[PDB]
């Protein structure tokens, strides 16, 4: 049962095996990470685990600029040059797709409503953590298999969720009047941390050699356009954060 102490014992044990023992064989790592995720997501949101695993992938695989010497092996032992490149990326991306789907569901049920305040606090918290996760992963060099197009699809879903959030804010800002400060920090964080590195990533993903990159540029420009409409329709300047 997901509230029992034996659940927590099993989760601690799984995570400890994940923290120590290497075992370079893709199927074993994949099934073991799937066990860990399966347990974790019925206990708490995995966003911390996604962050740490992205940090490990970034440290092991390296960066796009080939001048970042980062090693954070302490976090999770089951991250290898032969393991983390083909197989683990897909699993972490899949779980991130599931988290995006859950917040999409939240946003859609909140739109139809007009239970309010802590909901949006939790939503922006998950989105902030996922933004740091993505921040860590976008700077990495993945192989050009299913991993990269999966990353683009999930990033398109990310930007779509952001677009839907600012659209709900466009819906609500007339009735109440004002942006909650956590949303302001979240959009500031997206503007400062995410979007410039996203532009750098567009250059990086385009140069390395058809539909997802058009999807991504359309998504980001639509995000900026909806932010224009919000900054007009909110009587608050969110473009002093933007460039």
Image: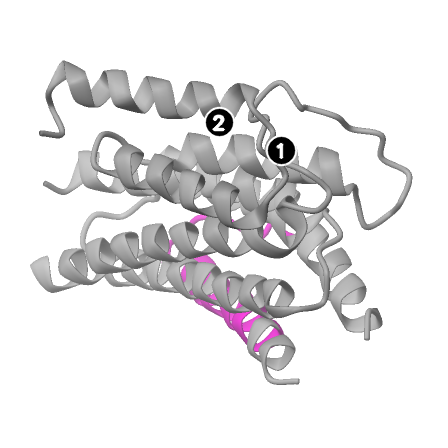
Q: Nearer the viewer, residue 33 or 221?
A: 33
> Does dot 1 land on a helix, a strand or a loop?
helix
Labels 1 and 2: the sequence-earlier one: 2
Q: Position of residue 232 (x, y in %)?
A: 44, 62
Give how far apart the Cα atoms at labels 1 and 2 are: 15 Å
Residue placed furthest toward the right: 67
Task: Specify whether 156 is left or right of 147.
Answer: left
**What span is colored magenta in the figure?**
217-243
Residue projecting furthest to the bottom: 210
Q: Position of residue 57 (x, y in %)?
A: 65, 39
The kind of secondary structure element at disc 2 is helix
- Identify the residue shown where x is 57% and y is 77%: 218
Q: Quadrant of the N terminus?
A: top left
Instruction: Identify whether 210 is placed above or below 8.
Output: below
Q: Nearer the viewer, mark 1 or mark 2?
A: 2
Q: Residues within 10 Å of mark 1 (few under 14, many from 20)?
A: many
Nearer to the camera, 171 or 30: 30
Q: Position of residue 101 (x, y in %)?
A: 30, 59
Q: Is residue 90 visible?
A: yes
Left or right: 234, with 66 as reference point: left
Q: Residues within 10 Å of mark 2 (few under 14, many from 20)?
A: some
Residue drawn at x 51%, y 50% as measured from the top left = 27
The residue beneath circle 1 is: 55
Task: Name which residue lies at 30% across and 24% down.
Answer: 11
Q: Which mark is residue 18?
A: 2
Residue 69, compared with residue 139, is above or below; it is above
Q: Which mark is residue 16?
A: none
Q: Main secondary structure of the magenta part?
A: helix
């Amino acid at each position: 049962e997901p509230s029992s102490p034996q659940f927590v014992q099993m989760l601690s044990w799984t995570s400890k095996i994940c923290k120590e023992n290497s075992r370079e064989d893709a199927l074993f790592c994949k099934s073991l990470m799937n066990l860990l995720f399966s347990l974790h997501v019925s206990y708490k949101s995995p966003v911390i685990l996604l962050r740490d695993l992205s940090q490990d992938i970034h440290g092991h695989l390296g960066d796009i600029d080939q001048d970042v010497e980062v090693e954070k092996t302490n976090h999770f032992a089951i991250v290898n040059l032969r393991t983390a490149a083909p197989t683990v990326c897909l699993l972490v991306l899949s779980q991130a797709e599931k988290v995006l789907e859950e917040v999409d569901w939240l946003i859609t049920k909140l739109k139809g409503q007009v239970p309010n305040q802590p909901v949006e606090k939790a939503i922006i918290m998950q989105l902030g953590t996922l933004l740091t996760f993505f921040h860590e992963l976008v700077q990495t060099a993945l192989p050009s298999g299913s991993c990269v197009d999966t990353l683009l699809k999930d990033l398109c879903k990310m930007y779509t969720t952001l677009t839907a959030l600012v659209r709900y804010y466009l819906q609500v800002c007339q009735s109440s009047g004002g942006i909650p400060k956590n949303m302001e920090k979240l959009v500031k964080l997206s503007g400062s941390h995410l979007t410039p590195l996203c532009y750098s990533f567009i250059s990086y993903v385009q140069n390395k050699s058809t539909k997802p990159i058009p999807n991504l540029i359309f998504a980001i420009e639509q995000y900026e356009k909806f932010l224009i409409h919000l900054s007009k329709k909110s009587k608050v300047s969110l473009m002093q954060h933007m460039k």
